[PDB]
Amino acid sequence: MLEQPYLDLAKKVLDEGHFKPDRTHTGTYSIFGHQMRFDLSKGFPLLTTKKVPFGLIKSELLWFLHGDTNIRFLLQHRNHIWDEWAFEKWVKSDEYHGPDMTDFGHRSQKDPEFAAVYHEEMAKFDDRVLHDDAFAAKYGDLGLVYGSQWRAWHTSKGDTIDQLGDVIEQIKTHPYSRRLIVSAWNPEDVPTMALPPCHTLYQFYVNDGKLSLQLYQRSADIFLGVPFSIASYALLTHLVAHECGLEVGEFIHTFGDAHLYVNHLDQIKEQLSRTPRPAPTLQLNPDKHDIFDFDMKDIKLLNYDPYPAIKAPVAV
Amino acid sequence: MLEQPYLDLAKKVLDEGHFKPDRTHTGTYSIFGHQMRFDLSKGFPLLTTKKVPFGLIKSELLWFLHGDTNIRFLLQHRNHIWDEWAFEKWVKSDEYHGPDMTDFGHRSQKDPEFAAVYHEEMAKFDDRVLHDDAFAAKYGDLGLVYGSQWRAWHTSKGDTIDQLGDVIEQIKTHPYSRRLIVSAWNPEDVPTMALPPCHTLYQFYVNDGKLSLQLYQRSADIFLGVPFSIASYALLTHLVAHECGLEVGEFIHTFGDAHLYVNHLDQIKEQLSRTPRPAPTLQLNPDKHDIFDFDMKDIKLLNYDPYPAIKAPVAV
Ligand SMILES: C#CCN(Cc1ccc2[nH]c(N)nc(=O)c2c1)c1ccc(C(=O)N[C@@H](CCC(=O)O)C(=O)O)cc1
Ligand SMILES: C#CCN(Cc1ccc2[nH]c(N)nc(=O)c2c1)c1ccc(C(=O)N[C@@H](CCC(=O)O)C(=O)O)cc1
Ligand SMILES: O=c1ccn([C@H]2C[C@H](O)[C@@H](COP(=O)(O)O)O2)c(=O)[nH]1
Ligand SMILES: O=c1ccn([C@H]2C[C@H](O)[C@@H](COP(=O)(O)O)O2)c(=O)[nH]1
Image 1: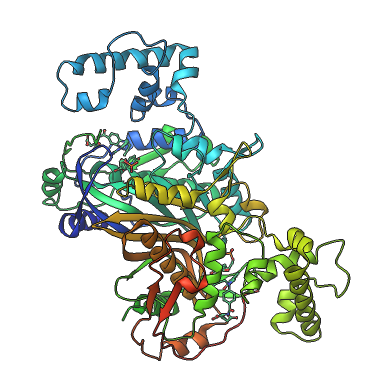
Image 2: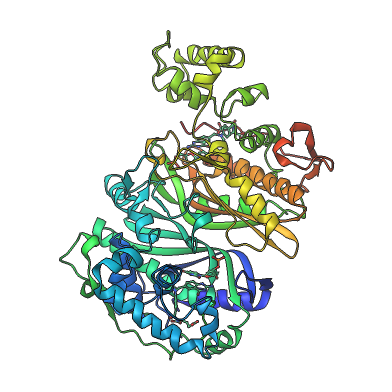
């Protein structure tokens, strides 16, 4: 079945995984070095053994493709994935008036009295952002994030570089290039950055008419962190191909520290019992071509037959 | 045997390798996505089925570790690997007086009348550099090269960042970090650069007391390009460990486009006949610790028993 590699990776870590403490102190079964591949021309590698929200993936990927970093677009799409990174500033501000949100993520992990206020103040910030146009401009904009990294590489002399764009250009002008790299790691922002990018760098490859891509990520939270990574990066491969007129090939996913949090194991042993069902089919709008405007209804997911959702706890 | 993975990779490309044209127009059997590992605590992965010059590797690696980019150090060590990248400027200059060296690399590939003059002018430039102190300052300095990338990351506001240093610092202050990355890919230099770095990015990993490293390279000239890459990056793993007081673990080598030039096949089929002999032993000076001054005689290679040298042609 199409997703097997991920179940094998999960399985693997569970066995030969070694214990490793965490920054956000927990334990983790970890492995260093691993590659898995999926032939995109055989189905979309969207996990069927667990409910995965393609809606979240798409909207998020379009945000990235717009080089947009303001949280407004995501909320607009009922997407809240990155909210916590905005809230961390809103609260660490002079304007913040209210429930001392210090370490709110951890306190809500088990959520006692802090629970309500945190999630209540959350509605606040998102209400503020979504409508207060100026608030959005200050607190909604995350700054350095995949989109700005991808399409707005802050140079040494003020100008901006659109890596992704100039890359598709590269694929078009001369596809057989070993220089099709889109780096997200900048040495000067990483030390003073909330969360250095996980999906660090990706390289495309054109041969026999098909487009293949390789994603390198220094860290991998296998339970909930990998199933999104796979899909999103498999989606980018159809978009580029469709843009450049290439037939989609296969997506390769290489990991630095691949791991399973110590408080995720029950849930993962649980998943390993179900058997994968036929891979979902991705459908792409034939009319529009400039992927940079390939909005929500331009990407359609056909016949996804997932196993129920397995809840787990945020890694704080 | 220790090197098997490389012979398997060679073997692989020869079989399921697909044809691919080149920038420097030749043909190439290519594969996209591949990882191979070596347990450094079992021997030094220095190929025994072909003579590999450890001298060249060391001197070159120390140049890198000094953040030095001037070709003087290399010539000083009887090392000429990077010369061609210096000559390309010396000749593309107002000062150049003599044999129009245009495309000298290609013309010398089959070397007719151009042969002598090119190699003669080469002695010239290197004689100039090695002794003419000021000449060295202008034409010897390559500018953007692994060393300066590693230890002199040109920031947005003039200052310089020593990635490698701050990284060993990271390994020391807190080893269990998934953020130990040393990137060599800079989005703004790559488009106006002679040869964008191949060995693009490497991440270390500390666990169970051992240091493991993963090297990502977008391109791999398997015949002569990989056997150096393996060794050099395996050497860096002993140096860091020895510096940080860690036991060496294993080195992981991941490739973007791994390939075998169409005019290298005979030589590679040739190699695949010999059987690997016990791996060489690396010896490290116990006294000095600051790897940045771990000079030539501080690294010793014990009992290397290689098969004879298989000549091949430079990929122009
Ligand atoms: C990926 C990504 C972007 N993100 C953000 C993101 C940011 C930092 C991180 N940090 C750590 N340590 N682990 C992570 O998984 C992680 C993920 C996500 C955010 C939420 C869910 C989610 O809604 N629920 C999960 C699993 C349930 C849970 O564990 O709470 C789901 O299965 O849908 C998934 C991904
Ligand atoms: C690696 C590296 C740095 N380099 C530079 C370097 C730079 C650009 C490149 N470009 C291309 N296309 N292929 C390469 O192998 C390559 C290598 C090297 C330079 C010379 C030898 C060498 O002296 N001889 C070889 C093989 C003989 C041959 O093919 O000519 C040997 O086996 O020692 C090896 C590596
Ligand atoms: O998109 C993301 C963001 C985070 N993480 C994981 C990686 C780690 O498991 C943890 C963050 O700690 P660091 O890797 O940054 O050290 O979150 C992911 O898997 N995917
Ligand atoms: O250290 C090096 C330098 C170059 N090459 C190879 C990579 C390619 O095979 C060719 C250069 O073409 P590009 O990959 O840069 O496109 O040289 C190596 O293997 N190692």
